Image: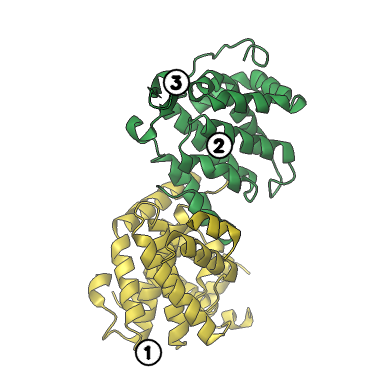
Amino acid sequence: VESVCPDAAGAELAWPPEEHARATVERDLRIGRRFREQPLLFELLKLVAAAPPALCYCSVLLRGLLAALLGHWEASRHPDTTHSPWHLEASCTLVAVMAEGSLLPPALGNMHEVFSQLAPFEVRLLLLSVWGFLREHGPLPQKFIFQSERGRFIRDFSREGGGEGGPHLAVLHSVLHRNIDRLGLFSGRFQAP
Amino acid sequence: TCWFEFLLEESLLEKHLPVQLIVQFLEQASKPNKRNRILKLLALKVAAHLKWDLDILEKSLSVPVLNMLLNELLCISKVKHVDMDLATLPPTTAMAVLLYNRWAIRTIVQSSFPVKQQMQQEKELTENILKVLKEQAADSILVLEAALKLNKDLKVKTEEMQCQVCYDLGAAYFQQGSTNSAVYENAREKFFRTKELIAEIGSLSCTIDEKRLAGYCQACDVLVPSLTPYSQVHIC
């Protein structure tokens, strides 16, 4: 966080409203450019996400990358997403990192696989759903209960209340329904259990 | 080639041989009795010239204009839908009722589809219509099921109409399947029925999306299995 986003004006771990994204366009675009220039940043994100509670402290970088991706998909005029490979892979890898750190439920964490078969506004709405879930729950270490049997912190989304993406999976299921001619075989990744 | 010209003569519609005419006639008729009745009759006549293809009317005409056209069709046909049962009703009235139910279920299914982001009044009217049909979606589903079950008999093939209505029912069940996983079994049954009907008839005529049907079948084969390394991995 210090190397990528040093100002840390929004250092609080919980996620703010999506209307705040336009207030910090410069900082989030700087974070996105830093990510684009250095592919090693994603690797360190995954290394941090290996420890469950550590990815909560990356919530600023996660929100900045999510906002940059959301803005690019807002500005993406292409009928598909294959014309922007870096942004598509950044969204996929950001979703993978967040789900790996157990900041997202598995039902809402399998969403990055269907990113490549979607037009920019579907993946934009999906990343907005990710932002909304991380607003409702928030990447906070206190939600992680240290399981002494194995020695690893465990994020129990069932105990959080609506942690399986109650209203957040509605957008994903609507996207699946709209593009059912291409997303039919991927319906097994977004089931409730 | 205007709204006023079409209302003058009673035979220029044959010389025209359309959706823009539909929206113009409906806007003129709904603007704040004989002229309105004539405009509605002309709109229904030109709408029937398209063989009542719901896809073109849905993609061209908006929600309130199509709702008004179908309400006028029902008013002139029969003039509550659940209790009709489509048993003793005339074939024209029964087909109009089932077409109205099919359009309603398609709109309630299509309303959940994400889309890219006078006008305010139209949006409010569409929202009110969507809420009203939400309050009466079960009645439409029951009417469609009864029509599919009652395959007693212008006049089109019974198999094509049954396939279309059961495809719409399966799409509705798939849309409803997100909240409850038990609804997917009915969706799978309806999709299998419409696939079998389409394979049996083999007639373009009516017209359904083959790719969408294949995607629905693939989704039902994995949601309720009752091949590819993908499906094998998920299943095991």
- For residue B97, above or below residue A97: below
In the rendered view, does B132 fall on the left or right side of B27?
left
Which residue corresponds to mark 2?
A127
Measured as percent of width and height from the top left, residue B94 is found at: 34, 80
Three-letter residue code for mark 2: Leu
Which residue corresponds to mark 1?
B153
In the rendered view, does A168 fall on the left or right side of B218?
left
State the separation of the CA atoms marked 3 and 2: 19 Å
* Residue at figure coordinates x 50%, y 61% from the top left: B219
| Residue A192 disc label | none
* Residue at figure coordinates x 63%, y 82% from the top left: B15
Which sits in the foreground, A173 or B22?
A173
* Circle 3 Cα neighbour tier, 10 Å, few/some/many (<14 / 14–19 / ≥20): many
Q: Is mark 3 on a helix, strand or loop?
A: loop
Q: Visible in this render: residue B1?
A: yes
* Residue at figure coordinates x 32%, y 86% from the top left: B90
Q: Mark 2 or mark 3, which is nearer the start of the sequence?
A: 2
* Residue at the left extreme, as displayed: B83
State the separation of the CA atoms marked 1 and 2: 50 Å
Give the letter of the yellow chain.
Answer: B
Quadrant in which the N terminus of chain B appears: bottom right
| Residue A140 disc label | 3
Which sits in the foreground, B54 or A73?
A73
Query: Circle 1 marks a residue in which chain?
Result: B
Which sits in the foreground, B51 or A34?
A34
